[PDB]
Image (tube, coloured by chain):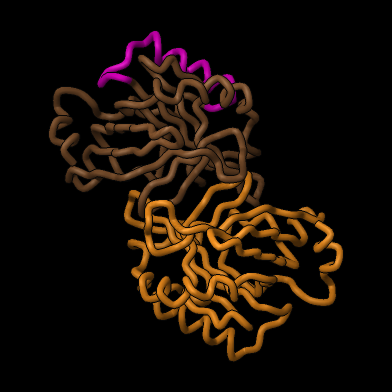
Chain colours: A orange, B brown
Amino acid sequence: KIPNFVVPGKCASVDRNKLWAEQTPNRNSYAGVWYQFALTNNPYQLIEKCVRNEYSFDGKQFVIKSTGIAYDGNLLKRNGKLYPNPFGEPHLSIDYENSFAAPLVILETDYSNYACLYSCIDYNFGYHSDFSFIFSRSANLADQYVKKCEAAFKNINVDTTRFVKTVQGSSCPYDTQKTV
Amino acid sequence: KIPNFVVPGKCASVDRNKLWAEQTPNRNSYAGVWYQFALTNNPYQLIEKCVRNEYSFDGKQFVIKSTGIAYDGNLLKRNGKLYPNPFGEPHLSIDYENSFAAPLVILETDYSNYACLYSCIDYNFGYHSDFSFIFSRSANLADQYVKKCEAAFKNINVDTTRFVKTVQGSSCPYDTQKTV
């Protein structure tokens, strides 16, 4: 029970089929660059600051190039993929090199400003861990969009006070990050 | 103050390239039924007792039907897949319906008696989590083979005192399990 990302109870039901209906035809619009505006405590994100995720869609998957400042303060690039769950479940799997793959539900997105992302894993002792993100198309994110994400996470009983803001903005060397 | 499967330092090098080469020509021999003899503390495994994993190989991946008795005392079947890591890394991904996918290394096997399996993940805070397993072609497994896996795990710095025996034997309803 001790870490704040280990939470009583089964992973939430999040109405995946409605979401998959909404999103499948708009995969093309989800490509491009997304900045990680905020996230809940995540022991698997190696990139601490200036997190910049670049998605290319190929018709079957997305290829991701994630860059930013690692926790030791150095530049870091991570290779990712985002593809339909291999068992035919109505969600995607997010898979990164030298890591593992997890379910990734887009709870809500307008494609042009924000996306609200959610992953959950169940334990055999009746608890779960989940990991949530707020993505923006820019370094900052208007309040109105931040509040949309807050509502979508509260709708599935994710405690939104768990979100922490990620360093973004003028202190980030994005232009270097894009060179890889 | 932390779980015994969260260990300081990084995942050790386990020479995957050598294993992968030895193992790609023998996929058909790895198919069939394997019984879980023992494992290290694993908060993801939903089957507690009588763990029986039936593998089928189709020429590109294994399809797995994993059955046994769940923590609640009911029979349980889980559908799983084991396929090459999607980035081209020299290990397999073990994937289960309604779960995540994780790297899985076959540290050692003779195909006809035993297999020693290993999964490890690095965190962002200077620790790793690893998950080890001893598999047998039968419900019991002779000391001769157990010792082989013990040596393999010790060779990669895993503390073998972490292994726990799984209930197997004439008490398990394997013929029911095989039927779903």
Left or right relative to B81: residue A82: right
Q: Is residue A157 visible?
A: no
Residue A13 position, x and y percent, is 34, 69
Corner quadrant of residue A45: bottom right
Direction from residue B102 to residue A14 in the image, left or right: left
- Quadrant location of the C terminus of chain A in the rendered image: bottom right
Report if residue A139 is visible in the image: yes
Magenta stretch in the rendered image: B137-158
- How many discs mark residues in the rendered view? 0
Q: Find residue B33 and report its image quarter.
A: top left
Looking at the rendering, which quadrant does residue B56 occupy? top left
Is B156 within the magenta? yes
Instruction: Identify whether B137 is placed above or below A7.
Output: above
Q: Position of residue B100 (x, y in %)?
A: 45, 51
Q: Quadrant of the N terminus of chain A?
A: bottom left
Residue A30 rendering spot, x and y as whole percentages: 59, 73
Which residue, as the protein is rendered here, is positioned at the far top? B144
Residue at the bottom extreme of this rendering? A144
**Residue A66: x %, y % from top left:** 70, 60
What residue is drawn where x is 33% and y is 11%? B142
Above or below for A60 versus B129: below
Q: Residue at x 54, y 57 (%)?
A: A94
